Image (spheres, rainbow, N blue to C red):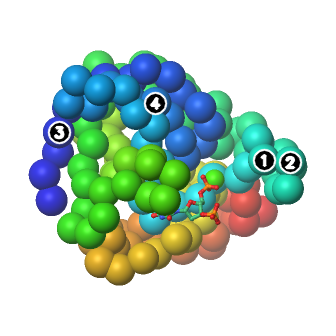
Amino acid sequence: LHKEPATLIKAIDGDTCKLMYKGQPMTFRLLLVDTPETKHPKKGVEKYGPEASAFTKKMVENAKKIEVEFDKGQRTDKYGRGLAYIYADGKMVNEALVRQGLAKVAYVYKPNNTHEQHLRKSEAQAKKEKLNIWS
Ligand SMILES: Cc1cn([C@H]2C[C@H](OP(=O)(O)O)[C@@H](COP(=O)(O)O)O2)c(=O)[nH]c1=O
Ligand SMILES: [Ca+2]
């Protein structure tokens, strides 16, 4: 994979944000994870939804550098959102959330699963530590 610079435009929730990428603004959705909903009426405000949003917001707003790393398959989803692993000062936001029990590993669609095992190992640790979503 290969990291590329991006500039934060606006944090939306735990797993979705707006970034300036290659000159253009677009919304990104974190690969392989799912933070709880705080927007869609069908799901309502789910437990830890507000917590995941705050964690992500803090993490991306305070970073000196943001980088996007597309996987080997499709780079956007059906809603036109970029699908990537996002790094804040070298730290993967996707992993950070999973490690804290603020996201579950989900939407594993091959071949966009390069970091699946890494994320799963962090999810298991969060589970055994009974963190947030796993408490
Ligand atoms: C992370 C991810 C989400 N999605 C889709 C699946 C879900 O579609 P449906 O909404 O049609 O079920 C939605 C989940 O994202 P949200 O967690 O942002 O809702 O985005 C992908 O298509 N591929 C991905 O890699
Ligand atoms: Ca979500």
| Residue 28 in the figure: left or right of residue 58 | left
| Residue farthest along the bottom direction in this orientation | 110
The residue wearing badge 2 is 41
Cα separation, mark 4 vs mark 2, equals 21 Å
Question: Label 4 amino acid?
Answer: Lys
Q: Quadrant of residue 28?
A: top left
The residue wearing badge 3 is 4
Cα separation, mark 3 vs mark 2, equals 34 Å
Question: Label 1 amino acid?
Answer: His
Q: Alpha-carbon neighbours of circle 2 within 10 Å: few (<14), some, or many (≥20)?
A: few
Image mark for residue 40: 1
| Residue 37 in the figure: left or right of residue 110 | right
Please determine whether, in this image, residue 39 is positioned above or below residue 128: above
N-terminal of the pair, mark 3 or mark 4, is 3
- Residue at 43%, 20% in the rendered image: 9
Cα separation, mark 3 vs mark 1, equals 30 Å
Nearer the observer, disc 3 or disc 1?
Answer: 1
Beta carbon at label 1 within 8 Å of ligand 1: yes
Give 92 or 29, whichever is nearer the viewer: 29
Question: Label 2 amino acid?
Answer: Pro
N-terminal of the pair, mark 4 or mark 2, is 4
- Residue at 42%, 76% in the rendered image: 109
- Where disc 4 sits, the SS reads strand
Q: Alpha-carbon neighbours of circle 1 within 10 Å: few (<14), some, or many (≥20)?
A: few
Please determine whether, in this image, residue 24 is positioned above or below residue 45: above
Q: Alpha-carbon neighbours of circle 4 within 10 Å: few (<14), some, or many (≥20)?
A: some
- Residue at 46%, 30% in the rendered image: 18
Callout 3–callout 4 Cβ contact below 8 Å: no
- Where disc 1 sits, the SS reads loop
